[PDB]
Amino acid sequence: TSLQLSIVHRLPQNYRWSAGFAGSKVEPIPQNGPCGDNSLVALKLLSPDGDNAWSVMYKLSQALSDIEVPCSVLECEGEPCLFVNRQDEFAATCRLKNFGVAIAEPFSNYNPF
């Protein structure tokens, strides 16, 4: 049902927080060698959108962070875009799917979980 499910990704890259803001910062890894599996992954704009899906997505990133799962949510105009750790891609879309909103997240290599 519906016909307006416009999902976009490109590549996760390996990036981190710039030790200034946490919740409002992103920067890549210029050849710095993290512990490894502690890269971040990022999501582009999605659709469909509405105040439901916005409010719920945001209230859920907060809720997930309340447990063990720091997720990041920022808009620009009409482009809600998202940031998660690593395994938190599949995990997030899995729990979010139950909440009924839409999401744009992959589930890592061919769903490896």
Image: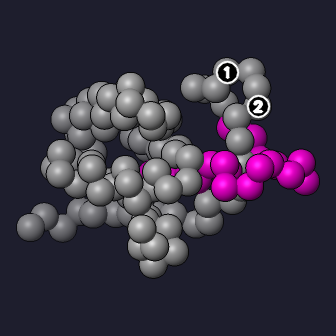
Rendered image quadrant of residue 11 = bottom right
* Mark 2 to mark 1 CA distance (whole Å): 7 Å
Q: Farthest right residue?
A: 31
Out of 17 and 79, give the one closest to the viewer.
17
Crowd band around label 1 with a 10 angstrom C-alpha radius: few (<14), some (14–19), many (20+): few
Q: Which residues are magenta?
A: 26-45
* Side (left or right) of 35 relative to 57: right
Relative to the observer, which residue lies in front, 48 or 70? 70
Residue contact between numbered discs 2 and 1, judged by CB atoms under 8 Å: yes
Q: Position of residue 63 (x, y in %)?
A: 32, 29
Magenta: main secondary structure: loop
Q: Residue at the spot x=56%, y=47% of the render?
A: 85
Residue 72 coordinates in the image, percent (x, y)? 49, 35
- 30 left or right of 6? right
> What's under tag 2, amino acid-wise?
Ser
**Residue with the mark numbered 1:** 21
In the displayed image of the protein, which residue is found farthest to the top?
21
Element assignment for label 2: loop
Q: Which corner quadrant holds the N terminus?
A: bottom left
Q: How many marks?
A: 2
Q: Dot 2 corresponds to which residue? A: 18
- The image position of residue 35, as x and y in percent, is 77, 50
Report if residue 37 is visible in the image.
Answer: yes
Q: Quadrant of residue 110?
A: bottom left
